[PDB]
Length: 125
Image 1 (cartoon, rainbow, N blue to C red):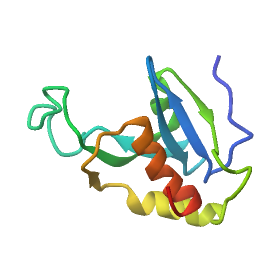
Image 2: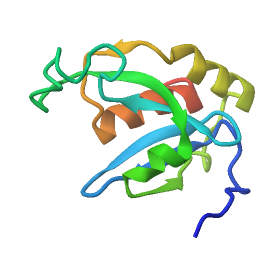
Image 3: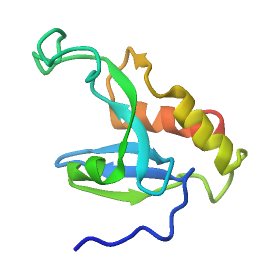
Image 4: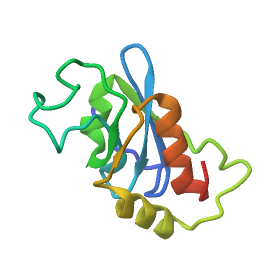
């Protein structure tokens, strides 16, 4: 059953459970997230190694949370809100949205997405 997400606030870390692993994102508005994605704004799924389903690249992207949640499941998980949050929500969101549209030359593993997104919430991975 669909439901709101009234506890989280823009600037919070989201995790995205996938069928056999997980992924990471950050909430940036009342429905949207910034996250790493496969190379999907550069090639028609037929002009990069994405066609071979074997690549070691990603892109920083923005999407509706409920599309990203289509992976399998999701949770809010500010991994160190128990210890730190040196940046206000405004700056966290501003960094997230400043960094959309670039490519990165590493795969979107759980570790690489966690690394990038922690750089937004806490200034450093």
